[PDB]
Amino acid sequence: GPGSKPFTLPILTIGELTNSRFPVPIDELYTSPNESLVVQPQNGRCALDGELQGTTQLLPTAICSFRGRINQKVSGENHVWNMQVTNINGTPFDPTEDVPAPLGTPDFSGKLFGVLSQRDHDNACRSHDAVIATNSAKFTPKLGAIQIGTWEEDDVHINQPTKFTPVGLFEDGGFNQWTLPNYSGALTLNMGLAPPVAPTFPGEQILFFRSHIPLKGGVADPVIDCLLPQEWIQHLYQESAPSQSDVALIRFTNPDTGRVLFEAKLHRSGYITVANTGSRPIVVPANGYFRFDSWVNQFYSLAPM
Amino acid sequence: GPGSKPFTLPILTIGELTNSRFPVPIDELYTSPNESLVVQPQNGRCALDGELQGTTQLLPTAICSFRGRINQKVSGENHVWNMQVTNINGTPFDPTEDVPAPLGTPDFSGKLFGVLSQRDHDNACRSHDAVIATNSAKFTPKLGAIQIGTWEEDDVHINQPTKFTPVGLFEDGGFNQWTLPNYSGALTLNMGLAPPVAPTFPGEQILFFRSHIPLKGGVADPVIDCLLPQEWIQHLYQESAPSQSDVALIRFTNPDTGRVLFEAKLHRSGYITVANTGSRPIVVPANGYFRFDSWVNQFYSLAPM
Image 1: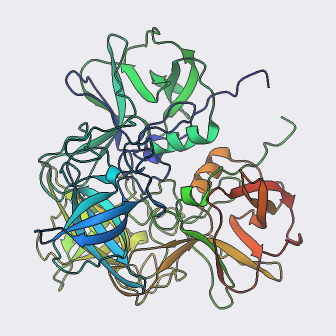
Image 2: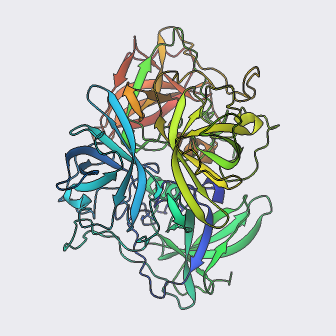
Image 3: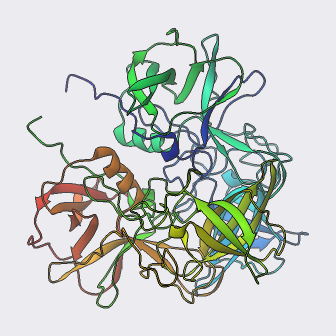
């Protein structure tokens, strides 16, 4: 009609949200100033009008997963395999397409721990622990191939349907959630990226949805922070509501109480800022959720958290 | 107002749906007659008005997961541990609550393969392969405890936060997707169950959303069939639209083509029937999705598939 469809978010509490950058539930909200770090995740990217960006796709369980077939054991390597990757649904990946990598590809540097599974054309199956170094020169998903390490020296089959189910990190050394992999390998620039995000208003910081992820060994508390929960992305994709301005004011509210705990800016490009100093984890009532209040601009002065 | 909010389903193709009974994408639609088998899944259960039933909860990645802490190594057992389970968000499980088990508990009998991870209070971490026999007398999630098997004899810590990430089945022997676990263990009846479902109209069969799941070893093609995709459940929970009759007519349609491929009955209790003979897998265009057409009754004669 003459009027626009009102923008909406799903009615979901902190305990009903999934991380859009790793297939686990959100544990908490978190805010910190990115003085040195540049924030440019490729998963969990979606404009408020429902446009998916970067490597973002809709399936929460498939985030950081891989699909394809093993073409060979890597030359001069025991326990390392070369995997030709397809899209998550099994359809061929189109390397010339204007995305950084197959949708769902991990968007952080480190050693990912998970399980490699196969079901051969004759239905003979196997699953073994595996590691994928997203920070290695031979991590080339954009070119259609990655390398996968196993402990099992021999029991991986060639030219058979293969999946990688992510579990967590193998080790904490070399892990940086904000360092993008080189999707095309060494000496090649990433392309088709979702843009970096930063709080434009002096005094604001990004608000993240944070998950603490598993670690195979070591002493650490590795976390993955996403800009938007996967359910919000799924919702925005469904709704495709036009954005009335560059910023939607949202209010975190407990429904039974009816009281608003704090307010934040949801930006058109798909991330949240708040007025806060330093980095502190945010604990919120299990009943509470973000409610859309109105459209404002970048110059709107938020109430301090 | 005086009028009811129109019922709706999400606009999602086959490749954009998640299984509600195991944390993997839907691979295909499937239909078969349950002449001998009784269909009573506890996950992926939701009335069309958004009422969650059985052990159904909202987080797709958390389906078939467990959370809690290891209290002891099992008496007379090497490699077997007793785990005191909490809810998925970590909050205490209320055994007296009218559910069959903690929400998200697996609803099938067999040996589940996955990874057990821990992060100790001092941040020392470990992850190891694990198996959970949902078909054992010591599987007692409703009582607040299960047993977990590992290969690692010693490297599991007591009284530390623990998670189980499911991957697939350990073996195919003993697996039956329609046999419910005894949630309270041997000699105790399940309670608070979602009711069994069956096609009431002579000549109809249930239509399932089917996934082929990983297997650690053996020759088999184990599948998990759900009544509703997880995204539909999330959507119905959000919408909470009143049901106008016992049956909603839905039409599977490819949007670009604009052509309807077939029609089905979406029942108020949350499952689909079609008019088909025997068991056959259904392949549908990647563009296609179910569209809600109108409300009918049990006596509506569907066009044959």
